Length: 9
Length: 10
Length: 226
Length: 235
Ligand SMILES: Cc1ccccc1OS(=O)(=O)[C@@H]1C[C@@H]2O[C@H]1C(c1ccc(O)cc1)=C2c1ccc(O)cc1
Ligand SMILES: Cc1ccccc1OS(=O)(=O)[C@@H]1C[C@@H]2O[C@H]1C(c1ccc(O)cc1)=C2c1ccc(O)cc1
Image (spheres, each protein chain N blue to C red):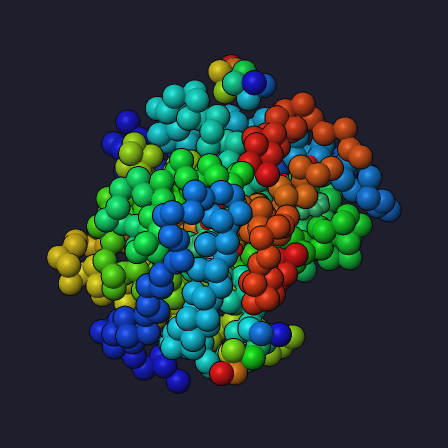
């Protein structure tokens, strides 16, 4: 869930 | 094409 | 000639050219369900072609150009009509007056559930906005001419239909701000209808049914780039 | 939370949130092939996605959404956003696509990978269409924000609540666009016409995205882990 992580900086 | 016919059809 | 039309003449022309609402052949397996839709869609295609000829500006195009627009926009046009028919039937898709389907019935075919929900979503979105028939016929014509133009005369006509849409909104007593907001809301929906069409044809050209020689001819137009 | 923005404030917000124009790795010594071409594009897109994610955070209204909804919008709109950015960069380079300042390609170089020249011509046609209408940067950043909030707004009682907020934001971006066109000295039928013209192009951008992704999830030349994750959302 990379996108999920990056959206959480 | 069959579509050609219908577009010129009466 | 279509450019010389007034906004009221535009609407009147578009309303008068409306295809009739056809009936389906009088539970569902994947084959029968697909059979009914294919038959219904095959029959509708004939009226759409005659409807297209009466869309102001469409006859001005070469036969090559007419065929191209129809090939690109046919499912979009079928879809917006369906969504419009299902206006006053929340939760259901009214494919025909004798064929009113819901989610669970859409699960009969592999991958159709997803498009059903989108179609239902578009319908309620139309319901929420109180989409009027005058606006609907304008939208449907836009689909025909815009899908797909980038695939000048057409843009002159597109501007005209835009003029008509705003003219309708001004008639209904909308303020200037409400006018462009509503215009935008309507055209953005067309983006989703395009999406539903593309995903729909993704499956359509993988399939069971007999499928019309005309219907396969419309499908073959989209396979060329699969 | 951000509906209290004037048009001018909306614009600078969008303009200051703009991602940079990233560079490729080519290298015009390498004779180029389908694999090299695809690698360049994949590496490029992948790095752009990181900037895109962080740009989205700065789009007014976006962070007011749940993380789930944020994920979904980006999963639906990423290629659309890459595409319109591509089309925008290439506005001053007719018959060419400026993937990067060092990666400028024509349709013939698009033939290097199968089924790509068709989308290439469409991207070209869109780029020219923008040049023809003389699209403005202010109009562009608005368009791109619209794509982000609209491409996956439809596709619970709380899920309908988030939808209404997005609609409020989109209407605010419409107003902004109209505001811009009005200041340019456009009439009113002109504003409405231009508004309609721009939004209709989003349909084509969606079309290119769908057809684009249709080819991408048939594959050779390893997609990045973030790109695979985005790509997986559309099966
Ligand atoms: C995506 C998909 C998967 C499986 C089967 C069909 C699929 O395509 S779909 O997106 O749902 C599509 C939508 C809708 O159901 C399909 C369909 C249609 C058209 C032709 C045909 O041979 C079969 C189906 C619909 C429709 C039909 C008639 C109308 O007047 C209006 C709309
Ligand atoms: C349709 C298709 C077939 C074969 C290979 C790729 C295909 O997709 S395409 O429509 O051309 C697409 C468009 C454009 O080239 C492709 C592409 C891209 C994205 C990710 C990837 O792994 C490979 C390509 C483009 C792009 C790239 C960077 C940008 O900043 C903006 C746009």
